[PDB]
Image: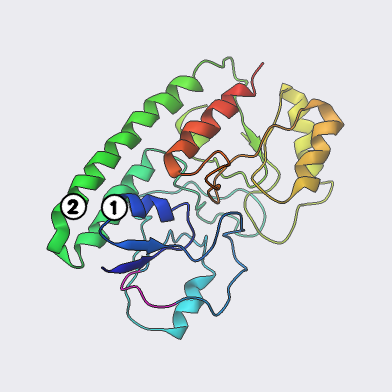
Amino acid sequence: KKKVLTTFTVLADMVQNVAGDKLVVESITRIGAEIHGYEPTPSDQDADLILYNGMNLEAWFEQFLGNVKDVPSVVLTEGIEPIPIADGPYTDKPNPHAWMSPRNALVYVENIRQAFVELDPDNAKYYNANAAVYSEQLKAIDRQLGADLEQVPANQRFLVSCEGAFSYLARDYGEIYMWPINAEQQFTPKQVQTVIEEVKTNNVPTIFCESTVSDKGQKQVAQATGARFGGNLYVDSLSTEEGPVPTFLDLLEYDARVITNGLL
């Protein structure tokens, strides 16, 4: 079978679910790791296809390709349209966390396909049979995600995080972040405080952060304003078989409740 490689994992399952049991897909990273760079060791490189997200997220390898030629990868993020970046370096760059909107995670499942059948169409009908299924499943959760965060008026719905990765999630439906994306560290006071204040202007309630490991940032505001510091959100990556979020779908299914569960 043809092997296939991904840029992280948030897409690893995404493709392994269209691939099915026909190919073999592997990521390069592993549960719980900043997919914004680092952890690049000799380990790698030959599958006959490499998929990725592009949009300067995961661009750690954009140079790493220099070690090899061909094995034509493919962006997936090509629908399309991005909402830009607010502050910090990469100002007015494309936000890249575009899979957290079920409506575009569609795109992929259709764009991902495209790259499959391009190579070894022997099993062209299998993807077509998978992608179509999945696609529904996606279209099905949308109603769940949309129907759950809808019962939270008035405005009180701006979810709060660190790597403000839900920029699309918040685009689809009814926001606050310590930093616009991963890079360097966490803006000092001037930064934190910026969230400290707006949490208490609206004025609640609980916020959220992403896996690890900028606890210093969000923690502080929790016990320095009037929060409760809800459980970790999932985006940059998946969780293990034990921890909630063993797959993409149930990631979405998950975060939405908890975001909604954070409302009085």
Residue 126, numbered label: 2
Mark 1 lies on a secondary structure that is: loop
Q: Is residue 176 left or right of 72 when viewed as pictured?
A: right
Front-lying residue, 232 or 171: 232
Task: Find disc 1 in the rendering and name its residue.
Answer: 20
Q: Is residue 99 visible?
A: yes
Residue 65 percent across, percent down from the top left: 45, 78
Pointers 2 and 1 in contact (C-beta within 8 Å)? yes
* Magenta stretch: dominant secondary structure: loop
Is 46 included in the stretch rendered in magenta?
yes
Q: Is residue 191 visible?
A: no
Kindly indicate the quadrant of the structure image that contains residue 139: top left
Q: Residue furthest front?
A: 242
How packed mark 2 is, by other alpha carbons closer than 10 Å (few <14, some 14-19, many 20 or more), is some
Front-lying residue, 95 or 27: 27
Q: Residue at x 32, y 47 (%)?
A: 107
Residue 258 percent across, percent down from the top left: 59, 28
Which is nearer the N-term, disc 2 or disc 1? Answer: 1
- Can you say whether 208 is above or below 66 in the image? above
Quarter of the image containing the N terminus? bottom left
Please name the amino acid that badge 1 sits on. Answer: Gly
Marks 2 and 1, Cα distance to the nearest angstrom?
8 Å
Residue 117 percent across, percent down from the top left: 19, 61
How packed mark 1 is, by other alpha carbons closer than 10 Å (few <14, some 14-19, many 20 or more), is some
Q: Which residues are magenta?
A: 45-49
Q: Residue at x 50, y 49 (%)?
A: 97
Number of numbered discs present? 2
Q: Is residue 70 left or right of 45 when viewed as pictured?
A: left
Please name the amino acid that badge 2 sits on. Answer: Tyr
Mark 2 lies on a secondary structure that is: helix
Front-lying residue, 96 or 116: 116
